[PDB]
Amino acid sequence: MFENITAAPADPILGLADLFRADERPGKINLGIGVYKDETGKTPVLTSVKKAEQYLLENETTKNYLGIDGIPEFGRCTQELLFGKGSALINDKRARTAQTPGGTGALRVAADFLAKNTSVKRVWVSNPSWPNHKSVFNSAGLEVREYAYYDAENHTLDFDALINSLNEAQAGDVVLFHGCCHNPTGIDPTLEQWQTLAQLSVEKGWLPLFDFAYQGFARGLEEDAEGLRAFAAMHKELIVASSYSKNFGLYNERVGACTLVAADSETVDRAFSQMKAAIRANYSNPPAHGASVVATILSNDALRAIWEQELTDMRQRIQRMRQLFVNTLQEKGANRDFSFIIKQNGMFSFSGLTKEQVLRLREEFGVYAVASGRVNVAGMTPDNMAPLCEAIVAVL
Amino acid sequence: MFENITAAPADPILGLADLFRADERPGKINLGIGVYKDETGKTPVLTSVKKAEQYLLENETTKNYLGIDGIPEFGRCTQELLFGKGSALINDKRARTAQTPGGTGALRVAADFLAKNTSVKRVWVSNPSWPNHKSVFNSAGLEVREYAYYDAENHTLDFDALINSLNEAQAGDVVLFHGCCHNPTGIDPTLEQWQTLAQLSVEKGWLPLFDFAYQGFARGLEEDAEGLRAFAAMHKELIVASSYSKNFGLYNERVGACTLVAADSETVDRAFSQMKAAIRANYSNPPAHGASVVATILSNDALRAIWEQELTDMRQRIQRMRQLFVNTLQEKGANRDFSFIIKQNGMFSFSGLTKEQVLRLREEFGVYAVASGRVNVAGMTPDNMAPLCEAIVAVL
Ligand SMILES: Cc1ncc(COP(=O)(O)O)c(CN)c1O
Ligand SMILES: Cc1ncc(COP(=O)(O)O)c(CN)c1O
């Protein structure tokens, strides 16, 4: 049965992890995978998480099944994060949340859902985008088409091209938008632009699907949700896949959620029972741990007050490294202007390096970055900034 | 988009959970979902698990991504459980394990794998079987056919009918076998029978797929694996989906694994890279917690010595309740012989109650059981045994 199986090519992102610990060469620098690192190049588990975990160890009395959609309070706390405590969506009971194994899992369950219970055939994804978007939607039998987004020359959001590309999407097609911290460009629409697309979207009849994996990494919790909230006030239905892997440092615990929004309580409820059926046939019910942690933190002011500060620290250190990288590059004689980098939000900078340059950086200097030239700024520290910048300069 | 969505019917198993806490009527008894309960009707978290969790809280320094196939030691410890420490499969490096969100998740990833990289079109499932088997395989686009298994009259394994049904399966079809504690009949093949099927399977060219969710609940760890081990010594390729939800009391942490076996190291490795691609497009990487616990327990003799005893206690209490149920039924004037129940292994007894009887038991007495007449013996206690038995007798 397996004699004919061809080997799949290594994952463009997760594959770097293998190569990185395959070459024992002293000063390697890992700027590939999107994981936060502190000034010492460590990925620590947050203090609030350690506190919440202790509490759980004290108070849990059972590991009995969670129920298909997970922990209620979790689902409730996430909607308030996404839509706002006031929000009519919450009051009209128009939204339903399922706890899922990470944002990726939320994208898959949404894909499986749309594929079996809807007439969706094609999903529109930005160009460029996170590489795994294609694979997830293709796994569910949906088709992926690309819409223009980034202006390489100016390092700008090519809005006119975005608008003009989307014009080929028909009523009933799904359009994927990144909530904030666009992966991998780091360029997001302004609120005015989010508004224009909110409206264009209602006239052309597209079903919006937001990928929210970095809430809190651009300007703040409530600000990063503005675009989504602009859409929810104007739309009757929409899906949102959010992740807690980055903003809670819970990467390997797989914590995320798929939020379904419909016209009214009765409708979202019917639609949701099918989403639950799709979960049952996939992984049955979600892993409790990571989600329990998030819920306990969110539910306790002391704990939540400490978390918001840890999040604020993460974001600020990244903004620091961002400006340092640019300054050291100019200091090291980079034959180019990299100022645009300071303008990007989130963990990544679309550096502009060519495939060949990133290949040489790795083989020659032990510097790891994604083929597309995406570099993890959050992996930069005052200690590796100089070796890194010299590697880059000797490659331009 | 959602105006037309029809509501999915409630899950035949997980749906009972809703109904049960929907009726506030004092003496309700829950014999539906397969969860272990101790003499006081509680589902406690195991002591070894509490110990392992404390250790993890002390020693974990990061929640960084786990890598598509999960924790190595976990994968390694599971293969030794399944195949045995000696085993040529392990020494020849013919097996590859992926850590997955529960046994259900392992069944899905195996389904997705077989569907995209193989010429499998149909999966053979016993009649009766765990209800979610159909849905998982149908989610992946595979077809499910049923093979005769249980003799209702005699409460025996209708081997001749089993053999005769399987004769319609062609070379290249997947046949699902339950390792031990057949859900829901509790009747398993003898080793001699496992042997006959091991051989019949090689001549007819079927790809075996074992569902192992109750290892340790029949007679013991190594004994419950005998059938599988009889097959692995005779087969060149096979897949095994195992679960740790019951034997480790880790239900909601979602801990299981999908083990792939091929002719040689080079082949299993090529095949496996595709299995990894299927995981990446589903949930990316598995939840660490539950699996870390299992690995720490398995890796430490003190901890593992305590676990094996807790498992032994669970199994023994069930065997106790099994004989008590039968004795109280006869004591309460049951107009029938229920002796066959003592002969069944695992958590469930196929009682023989009709759909109508189980419907009446619920509405009239607050006694919850699955439509098929499957009752959770592990949910019986000396305290509810009498109310329960009277409910049943007044329904025969
Ligand atoms: C845009 C985007 N969407 C979803 C995810 C998947 O996140 P998770 O690791 O939570 O599964 C990521 C990973 N960073 C992402 O960048
Ligand atoms: C036969 C069988 N297979 C798989 C599973 C799924 O187990 P999990 O809860 O580990 O996902 C179960 C549930 N008891 C089962 O009974």
Image (spheres, coloured by chain):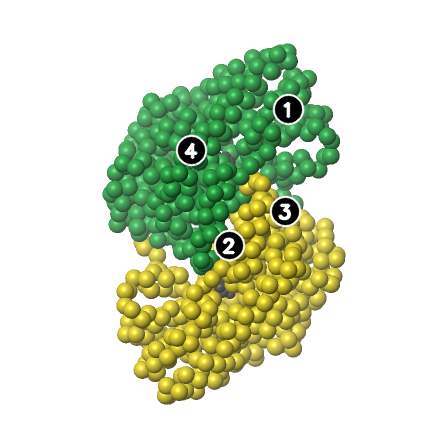
Chain colours: A yellow, B green
Q: Which mark is residue B384?
A: 1
Q: Are marks 1 and 2 on the same chain?
A: no
Q: Are marks 3 and 2 in contact (CB under 8 Å)?
A: no
- At a point 47% along the width and 32% down the height, the residue shown is B310
Contact between marks 4 and 3 (CB within 8 A): the answer is no
Q: Is residue A256 visible?
A: no
Mark 1 Cα shell of 10 Å, populated few (<14), some (14-19), many (≥20) = some
- Dot 1: chain letter: B
Q: Quadrant of the N terminus of chain B?
A: bottom right
List x then y, in percent, for residue A241.
Answer: 57, 59
Q: Amino acid at mark 3?
A: Ser
What residue lies at 43% left-to-right and 87% top-to-bottom?
A337
Of the residues shown, which amino acid type is indicated by label 1?
Answer: Asn
Q: Is mark 2 within 8 Å of ligand 1?
A: yes
Please state which of residues A379 and B377 is positioned toward the viewer in this rendering: A379
Q: Nearer the viewer, mark 3 or mark 1?
A: 1
Q: Dot 3 corresponds to which residue?
A: A273
Question: Quick one: label 1 or label 4, which is nearer the N terminus?
Answer: 4
What amino acid type is highlighted by mark number 2?
Arg
Mark 4 element type: helix
Q: CA distance from mark 1 to mark 2?
A: 39 Å
The Cα atoms of the two marked residues, 3 and 2, are separated by 23 Å
**Amino acid residing under circle 4:** Glu
**Are the residues flagged by discs 3 and 2 from a single subunit?**
yes
Which residue matches tag 4?
A: B308
- How far apart are labels 2 and 4 at the CA level? 29 Å
- Mark pair 1, 4: CA separation: 28 Å
Circle 3: element type = helix
- Residue at the spot x=54%, y=74% of the render? A316
Q: Check contact, mark 2 vs mark 4: CB within 8 A.
A: no
